[PDB]
Image 1 (cartoon, rainbow, N blue to C red):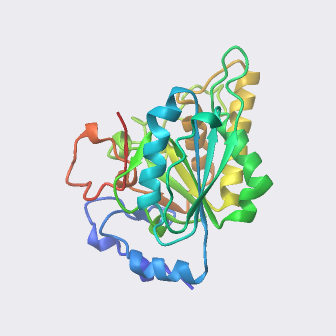
Image 2: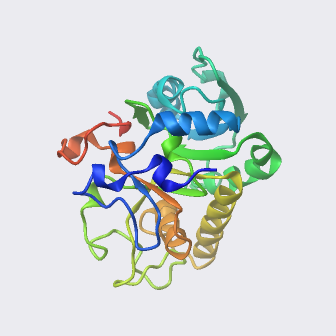
Length: 277
């Protein structure tokens, strides 16, 4: 089956990191053959799930545009299930999906104290993986709703565990990274240690990887709640801890998640996804 040479060529992008000291492709525009993989993956009849939580104001601010963009650019030409998690199914924008997309919607409870987090997405995702997603898909992406697909976000992103380089900090040094530094947090990453700064707005992998990613992240949040402590960037900090203990088998370039208000540096040749309004 697939080997990296078949789909991935680092030397079409030599400026940027394209491989990692543990041999994981960092996927950049111009570095990947979608055609090959589209073909390779279509034969295996893979199915890609996309979870996205949207809660309160976020539902009407973002969901419609998310699902619409996804419908157009996410794993085009492969079955894709959108798992929409919302607090209020009444205001589900409920767009028109195209070939190979379908969705499942789930009512989630809002943030239950007082004031929760609210990620808690980690517990729900893992719950859903066990209940149905492991049965439903070969690869699952978990994404923040307040983003937009700008171009093909395809099977070049697929892998055992897939992480996204947060746009700001992709050039940064490991010790500039906004990891949780407080040794009391389960999310704790020493200064010194640190591979990349991973964005929580997109992680993915097989349902089994993602189950573990999420179960570990949640255990982190949970132990932190027990120690009345709250990681700097909440779930993104645990993700970063997790992805340090467990190196992602594939990493996506800030091109797969770009903040347009960080500009447009040459290094960003096609924007697959971007943050919104």
